[PDB]
Amino acid sequence: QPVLTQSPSVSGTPGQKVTIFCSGSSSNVEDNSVYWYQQFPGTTPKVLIYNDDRRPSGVPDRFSGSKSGTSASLAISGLRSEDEADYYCLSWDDSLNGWVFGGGTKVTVLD
Amino acid sequence: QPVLTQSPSVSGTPGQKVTIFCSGSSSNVEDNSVYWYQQFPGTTPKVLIYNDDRRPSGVPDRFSGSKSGTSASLAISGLRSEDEADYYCLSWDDSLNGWVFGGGTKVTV
Ligand SMILES: CN1/C(=C/C=C/c2cc[n+](CCCS(=O)(=O)O)c3ccccc23)C(C)(C)c2ccccc21
Image (cartoon, rainbow over all chains, first blue to last red):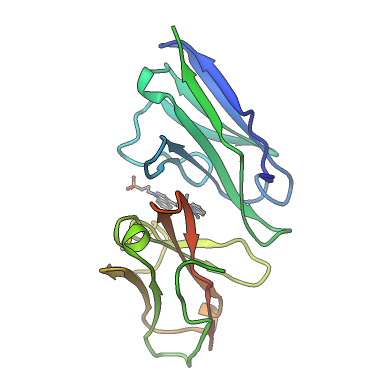
């Protein structure tokens, strides 16, 4: 099982602001840099957020990240159809001494 | 076992320029971004290199990374007892559809 907890699936319509969550513990999320990535089926992930809240140049400005204690979050401010994908969080874990991951949150853009 | 190949260890003495190697395949190292991190004992890892050869701000120009074909390397110019950590490469792998890692190169000064 993934050591970090993400809700498996979220829906929304274009334009809606949706935030997804990544819950960990004192020995991971709380403690350590959190990274988020976006994965479409069959292709290489795109890093959306590194070091908790930093957005690479080239990632659309509607994506932002932050960390509140044992919980990290990724906000998508104005969902687009092209945002339908699987979103993962990860960080180092002090107690397992290696990388830990959420199980991914699949975002569906409806209408 | 780690999918990328690294020397399990590499001893050295202050002053000299060491090089850590990381070999993989066309579906990982060649076709994907390589990252390097450094892990001191009981300390959170620091990324020294992203996208093959770029340094995060706050990382001494004295680490450099690069790659050719299916292998990557991190050159540590001008050692220090401070640089005594375990150094790791990683990248996405298209064939496994997942992340792959080197086994780490424990540097000794
Ligand atoms: C540790 N780690 C990872 C780190 C990724 C780090 C960074 C990814 C992208 N940028 C680019 C932003 C600058 S720019 O490109 O906008 O100029 C960075 C910049 C500075 C430091 C780190 C990064 C990934 C790869 C997430 C990963 C995956 C699996 C396990 C571990 C693991």
